[PDB]
Amino acid sequence: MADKLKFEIIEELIVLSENAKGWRKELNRVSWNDAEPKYDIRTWSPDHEKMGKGITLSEEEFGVLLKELGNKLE
Amino acid sequence: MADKLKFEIIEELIVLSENAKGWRKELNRVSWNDAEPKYDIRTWSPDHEKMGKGITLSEEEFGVLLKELGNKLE
DNA sequence: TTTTTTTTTTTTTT
């Protein structure tokens, strides 16, 4: 929506890689407008010049999600 | 975009819960237009009457993502 | 080869 949305990287979680479009797929915990810190997984430009839209994962989600996912690899 | 997008549930992976909006947060592998089967995490209506937008996770992503995330809870 | 959102969306043949 806005040209530059306010944010801040609280903690880097997982980094996957770039795609054919250069989409840097990563999962990091950032603060929404430098207020609420939460986990959000998105992909950005290869040159890190811009960002895109993905999905936000709350503690409730990440908790149950990781619990099951981690156990799925068992 | 469309009123009803074509799809098919190949395999259910993880089910989180509903939210204050009734958003049923789940992660299941479905076939895009009943063609390409891929993992996609989204939230639907409480009464499962409609669906919404989320994010699609490819094998490359889910693979590295799971590996790291699973190890993160170790 | 999307141009990111301070928690009641109406889903897309990579």
Image (spheres, coloured by chain):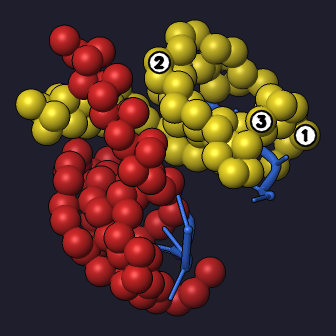
Chain colours: A yellow, B red, C blue
What's the mark number on residue A3?
A: 1
Image position of B33 with respect to A43: above or below? below
What residue is shown with label 3?
A: A46
Question: Residue A65 lies in what quarter of the image?
Answer: top left
Residue at the image point whose x is 30% and y is 53% from the top: B27
The chain holding disc 2 is A
- Dot 2 and dot 3 residues touching (CB under 8 Å): no
Percent x, y for residue A69?
Answer: 21, 36
The chain holding disc 3 is A
What residue is shown with label 2?
A: A13
Mark 1 residue element: loop
Give the Cα distance between marks 1 and 2.
26 Å
Q: Amino acid at mark 3?
A: Pro
- Which numbered disc, 2 or 3, marks the residue closer to the eye? 3
Q: Amino acid at mark 1?
A: Asp
Percent x, y for residue B47?
Answer: 25, 72
- Which numbered disc, 3 or 1, marks the residue closer to the eye? 3
Residues packed near mark 1 inside 10 Å, few (<14), some (14 to 19) or many (20 plus):
few
Query: Residue A25: in sight, yes or no?
Result: yes
Residue at the image point whose x is 39% and y is 58% from the top: B40
Counting residues from the start of the chain, the first of labels 1 and 2 encountered is 1
Residue at the image point whose x is 53% and y is 14% from the top: A12
Residues packed near mark 3 inside 10 Å, few (<14), some (14 to 19) or many (20 plus):
some
Mark 2 residue element: strand
Percent x, y for residue A54?
Answer: 58, 46
Of residue C9 and residue B35, the one placed in the foreground of this image is: B35
- Which numbered disc, 1 or 2, marks the residue closer to the eye? 2
Give the Cα distance between marks 3 and 1.
18 Å
